[PDB]
Amino acid sequence: VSTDTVLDIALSLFSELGFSDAKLEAIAKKSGMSKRMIHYHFGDKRGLYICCLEEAVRRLRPTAEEMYLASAVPVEGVRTIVEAVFHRYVQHPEAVRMLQMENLHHYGKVAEASPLSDQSAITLQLDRLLMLGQDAGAFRPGISAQDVFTLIASIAVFRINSRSTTLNLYGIDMMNGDNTDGMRRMAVDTVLAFLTSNLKSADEDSYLSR
Amino acid sequence: TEVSTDTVLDIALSLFSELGFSDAKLEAIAKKSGMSKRMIHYHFGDKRGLYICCLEEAVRRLRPTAEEMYLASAVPVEGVRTIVEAVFHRYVQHPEAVRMLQMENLHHYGKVAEASPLSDQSAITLQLDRLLMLGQDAGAFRPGISAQDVFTLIASIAVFRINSRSTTLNLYGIDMMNGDNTDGMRRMAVDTVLAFLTSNLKSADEDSYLSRP
């Protein structure tokens, strides 16, 4: 068994049962790696749990290869970024539930802790793209790469997270084929309309600040 | 001096949204509420009965009233702005109701997806469908967007601020729940919805983004 194999089995259990119910013996039985050797690479159970959160962030982060586009047109460039990001959320729902587990029960108290990953990658490629479109007169000022990413993540995560309550209240399964395509369309059309809007906005240079 | 059904429902909703169904104990709810564990079983039946009553309460706390839904200025754009800000405000005022519903969406304690609806949300949908219909005929809004599409877009932003606050603060150093960012998330919800409805960009021949068979 490899380090990536144990990390995959552990991520699935933590995203389904939580930190309390997911047992190391159950992970050792499925992974094939002894509980003693799991402690050697990942450390204690909380050490393995934080590795799963770092993996969850990594699984949801698109590569520069997945976001490359020859077409200089900033509109089609942003479309590629949105669809690339959204696709990873569709392919990794276990990574989404993994991060949502931490956001509900703060098992790792991650908010006041060391960053899980260096996300200066997808932000830099998007900031440059928004900068080119703004000077070309294609996009309006006041929107940062972090604002665009938050808008994409909000839609991509809501599909997986609020699936059960939406299906109960409105009879809509956001995770079926048709609705997974519709949520992608909503993410693309919402972002592009937001960037190319002629409506009057606040004198603020960003929606989210740090 | 006597505890009420609404009082026990409030204490129970807070524990379930923080600790979950497993850790939140009836003895802890009885100690805070003042109502005996025996009398809590009399009104709510069992612990799962009390849990489902908390989910039903969580939905009505995030449902804006008809008074908040009434648009004063008869403008399609300003009318939608009032709906977006009214919905977003209830999410800001009731983060415990948001975590309550997210508890069910993660661990399906009440298997709510294949169960009786928690609340009749058809009244809020019928009013927004009328406002989008008036704006579409007035040439203000584009076709292909339903009230359910608009509500999903508002909820996505309003919920993300709460349910993804800790990871965002760790990865990007941004507290979406602080004053400045709570205003920015509201601005994003308003500007995003209005831009989406008034977009001149080419869209699919589909009459809705989300569908229901």
Image (cartoon, coloured by chain):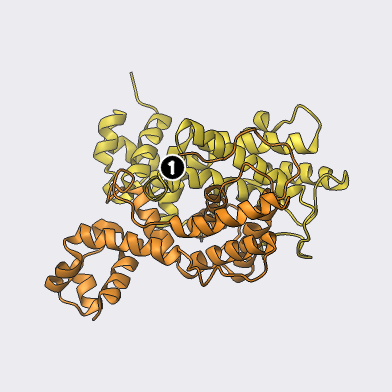
Chain colours: A orange, B yellow
Which quadrant is the N terminus of chain A positioned in? bottom left
Chain holding disc 1: B
Q: Does B77 sit left or right of A116 as displayed?
A: right
Q: Does A73 sit left or right of A164 as displayed?
A: right
Residue B64 image point, x, y percent: 61, 35
Residue toward you, B208 or A198: A198
Name the element at disc 1. loop
In percent of the image, x 67 and y 60: which residue is there? A74
Question: Callout 1, which amino acid?
Answer: Ile
From the viewer's perspective, is residue A65 above or below residue A16?
below
Residue under pointer 1: B174
- Number of on-image labels: 1
Q: Residue at the left extreme?
A: A36
In percent of the image, x 34 and y 68: which residue is there? A12
Give the image quarter of residue A9.
Answer: bottom left
Residue A71 image point, x, y percent: 67, 69
Residue toward you, B124 or A68: A68
From the viewer's perspective, is residue A173 above or below residue B28?
below
Does residue B61 appear in the picture of this structure? no
Residue A181 image point, x, y percent: 63, 67
Residue B205 image point, x, y percent: 79, 65
For mark 1, does the 10 Å Cα neighbourhood hold few (<14), some (14 to 19), or many (20 or more) residues? some
Give the image quarter of residue A70.
Answer: bottom right
Which quadrant is the C terminus of chain A positioned in? top left
Does residue B81 appear in the picture of this structure? yes
